[PDB]
Structures are given as C-alpha cells and as structure tokens.
Image (cartoon, rainbow, N blue to C red; front, side, top):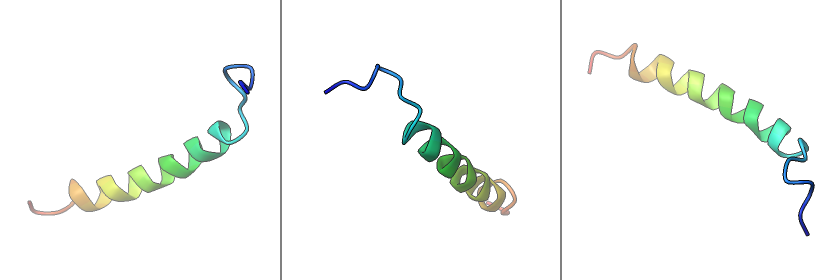
Length: 34
C-alpha cells in the first residue's frame, strides 16, 4: 500500500548513506591525474 507518498523512513535514512558514498567517489575521481 502507499505510505503517504512521502514517508521519510527509509528515504530519510538512505539519502544520508548516498551522500557519504558520493563525496568519497569525487575525492578519488577529481583528485586523480586522469
């Protein structure tokens, strides 16, 4: 069933997890020579 079309349960939990993975990816891609 629908969960109010928003429900900040897993969304508000997974959004922070993604933020941590993106910052580490940029620090290794942009900071590299090529």
